[PDB]
Image (cartoon, rainbow over all chains, first blue to last red; front, side):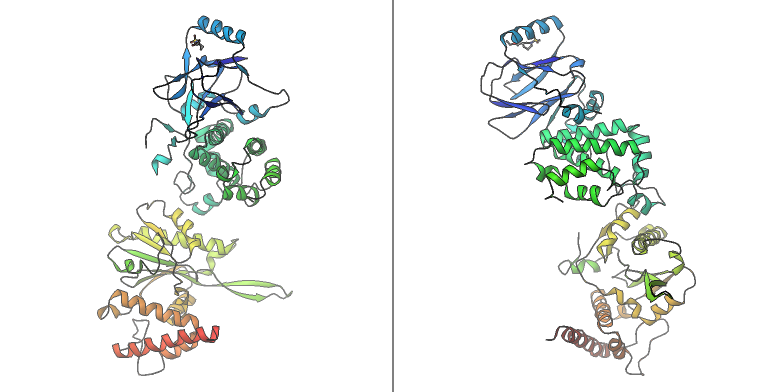
Length: 300
Length: 237
Ligand SMILES: CCOC(=O)[C@H]1CCCN(S(C)(=O)=O)C1
């Protein structure tokens, strides 16, 4: 179990750690979070009490170093930092654990939600999508744009997600125009799986990262990517049996963890009514379909 | 964007453009089988690709043979239309390729866009107008060449005959549409009008009779009357 301590909490903010959150008052005694499970990526995120504009957050992994949060009053946000000094670190964290100034990452033991949402997500790939290499952790917020969006403006603050475009040359083999556009198997399996992602786990990982950035930060370009990558599999007649099974589990938990009052903006009607009821794989997503009908039949 | 009454005069500027109509590409005759079931038998179709400014018609003949052994023919007809339109463009010299292509049925947007991925500077557009190009097969010479063809075949026409010698594009297009609209609403009568007077003839290299200008006004009037009526006959007013 590891710890993300805080130098202080100068402004009133709601802090999130993975799917958990808690309100901190202006200048409340508060030196961070403890008991964070090792072996998963995490994200710790922020929504100021004054300006609900700009949710922002840091993806990180406790194995890749010691990371703490001091507020920056010039830039006006909680920043993630990384010390070297192991010994200064262990002993200062120990001080706060002693005065009990940290909240406990509150994991119920029966619960595998986080594992399920982040099964295939690895910090190595996150850092390729969010380019900023002097830091072991990755900053994301509400308004960052994707590589594909800037095609249609600041590249440093982009999310360099894999570009998917159904009406593109990459996706459509000359001479198979109609075949490749109504059965994307070629695009999924050869171009993307064999070509760009190499295996389904890097694919699924980008999928899972996109959705999490949509949900936590309401990043619109992320929700587009999540939806595109779902659509490409469901519109593929030929998908390995194991991908179809894993995808059903994956989506199931993403739909499970979505806030019920957020479904109007983060869920795309066309994509889901197609994946669930028209696409090749309309029969292959039993758990995902079952929960979407019991929880969001309005959309359908 | 979409094409409608408001941006109506763009068709006649100097940017090359083509209308594509696909109604008559997949044509069937629904019959009864010996067992008392129903089957379709296909007959020849055409893609009606037309330059509304010059009146050049690229009449691509779709021969029944193209459907042999295929499923979901109504759906394939749209992709086959897109494939033939894209090859026509490829065959044209660059200075002749259209900058725009207007499909008369919105179902053709995606098939063409995909077949035209190599032509990003050509804009594919739909339209809000209810144009009557379906009636193109009521033009005898056009029906004739289609039904007689024995293999795939492109056949070039000018749908305006010689009109442009005396009238503007704008006006030529309004006569074409007024003629097709009448042929669509009541073919028999429309044709009776065009060929009542045996003294007016159809030159062998034309599609429509050789009317003088005065005759064309008389003829145009009579077509408008027909179109109004069949709207009464149909709606009781
Ligand atoms: C009283 C304010 O506390 C702090 O500033 C410490 C808690 C964060 C951890 N560090 S460290 C590891 O020494 O860089 C500083």
